Image (cartoon, rainbow, N blue to C red):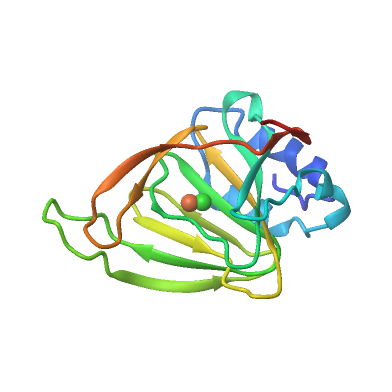
Length: 186
Ligand SMILES: [Cl-]
Ligand SMILES: [Fe+3]
């Protein structure tokens, strides 16, 4: 029985219930993420920005079933075109707007990766992707407003692939944390 999360802490408790088993009800998870109304005081501890690129700030390790983290995107900061390592990936905007561009998996032939679609994700909205849907790039295209998003990955993963938009060629990247549980982790 899904109830509205009253706070970030309440959301986390509810997520631990939704991930208590071995499968994932994507629609329920997305609905509860969407229902949490972003309250900046509740997540200020995790919102640690870097001047030069977006940061990943671990919030909860989900008893091993998921990683929940907050990503902080300066003006103009964005990702590579990337996959999600056979995991579910949920993205909820806490502050600002992000542009999500979708791409198909490349063929073996070296070719330009052409976007399949794009959308602007707005405050409090929750998007979802997995490798069966495709690849994406996520970008804060604003010149004036930093963005903050809440990401849930299940199972957790610490590597993924970045794709060269010119060729479709992929390279494995290891994902790093800027902080964990509010503590900067050099
Ligand atoms: Cl993502
Ligand atoms: Fe992603």
